[PDB]
Length: 119
Ligand SMILES: [Mn+2]
Image (cartoon, rainbow, N blue to C red; front, side):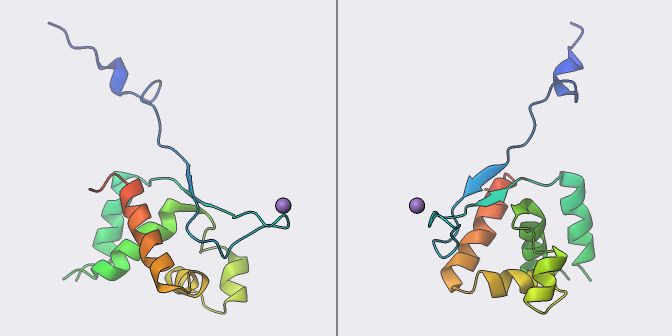
């Protein structure tokens, strides 16, 4: 019954969010309002290169952290400005120094994992 594939193509398939989430109340702007993090799922292809990139035996901790860094649009921990200021070229370390309250860091990770449709 000739199947209609237009729905699974770019000129159509609704695209992934850009979800704002207030990961921490310690980040505020000039007007005292919380600055939420902006997340946006990465691609399945990309999650694949990351897995490969962290396997030898997979470093999950590292794997997930890298996913979170890339799923996080604002702030992006790869930004030169953040690497400079926090004095580390490791975007995952930048994240640990920025989300310096345990719970925030754990929450950020999970939101990212969630934003990518996992569980
Ligand atoms: Mn105000």
